[PDB]
Length: 46
Ligand SMILES: [Zn+2]
Figure 1: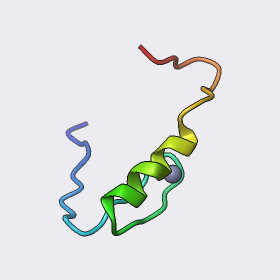
Figure 2 (figure 1 turned 60 degrees about the vertical axis):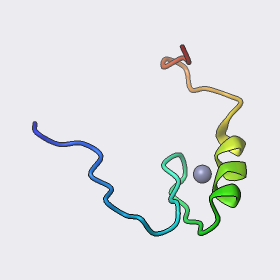
Figure 3 (figure 1 turned 180 degrees about the horizontal axis):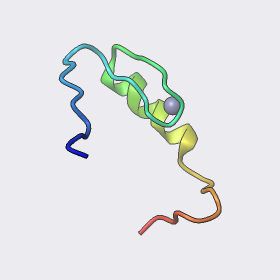
Figure 4 (figure 1 turned 30 degrees about the vertical axis):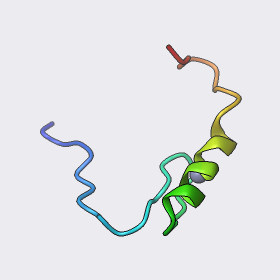
């Protein structure tokens, strides 16, 4: 149904892979990497 990523939060940066929170973009970027590596059987990167 009509729905998606509303977000609308210009306060820090929250992760979607795990669900954490950050304040410094950089710190938020170096965090999204930890997830970058292995992928679950099924959905592959394109
Ligand atoms: Zn994360």
